[PDB]
Amino acid sequence: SRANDAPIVLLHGFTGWGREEMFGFKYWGGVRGDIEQWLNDNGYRTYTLAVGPLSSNWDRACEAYAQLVGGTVDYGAAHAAKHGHARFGRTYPGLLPELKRGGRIHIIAHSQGGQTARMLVSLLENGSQEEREYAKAHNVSLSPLFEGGHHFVLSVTTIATPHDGTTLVNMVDFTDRFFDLQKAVLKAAAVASNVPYTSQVYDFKLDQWGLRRQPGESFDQYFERLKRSPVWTSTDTARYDLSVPGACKLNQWVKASPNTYYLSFATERTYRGALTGNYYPELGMNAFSAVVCAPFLGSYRNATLGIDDRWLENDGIVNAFSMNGPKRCSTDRIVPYDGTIKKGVWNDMGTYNVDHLEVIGVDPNPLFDIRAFYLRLAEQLASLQPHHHHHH
Ligand SMILES: [Ca+2]
Ligand SMILES: [Zn+2]
Image (cartoon, rainbow, N blue to C red; front, side):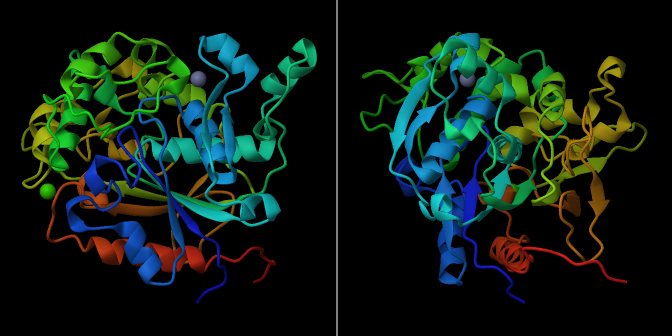
């Protein structure tokens, strides 16, 4: 039964766009429909965040914070100075000013969104010592996000999140293939990559880096430029955070708040080979991933990275092992869901037989009741109690 009225906020990964983008084709729903609408139609107030898909989780967290409460994005003086990008970014009206007044939210996150949501919680709750220290030392102002003390988040749910990174980054042609994945997703939405559309269509939101698709430029061409840009070559990137070492570094500081409930969903769409311990893409997996990424994921080992047989099972984009919660370079705790949802630890909800894109409806799969999945989830989140008392 319903113990909380908090709104839900959807958060995309290394691929994603706002509701008005991509000619209305939604990331949360894809060919299946409008997940946000379904949830709202069903009594679950839901909103959608849209942040830089290729940007660092930090940047995304800063973007999210402003998008939620409103204002100009502030990445932090220290950070900015460190990485060489703008301190201030775009301005938002603010989706939920109730947060400033004392409300809370449930964040449902997909892919790299998981990492972002985690970071956002940590920043809200703890701030950034490094940003505070930098402020006092250089006499610059400080965003509230870096102070600590915010209690905006009741829960964080992650679906197909590379909490320990993904070996996808280790392919020799990764750079080219990653961008081909963006093209695939455009394809899914009925958008071509070799057309210089005048309308924006997919805004990567690279204001901080001063990058934007130029008049007369196709996504194919733009992507060529992005590959040689700081959003691809610097450590302040999704690319870095997606990596095993990257995710490790992130886990080192991004911890679970004892005040927040976390839920994790894993995804897999592979089968185990006969004579080899390798995993292969199942029938139905999205074409792109099946041909281009899944073989690699299902067969790549690396002792120095600790990539062993456990990491081979995948959803075509991310290793299933890296999905139940941060384990590499982490103090976070993960507990198998047994019926009761626990606060301050990762409630591992299991593994579902759906691929990376099928789970958000961007790739079809008729045997996966996507509406039911998200509706059940909503019901769960709504059932969370603000507080607990010990009992037998
Ligand atoms: Ca499919
Ligand atoms: Zn940055």
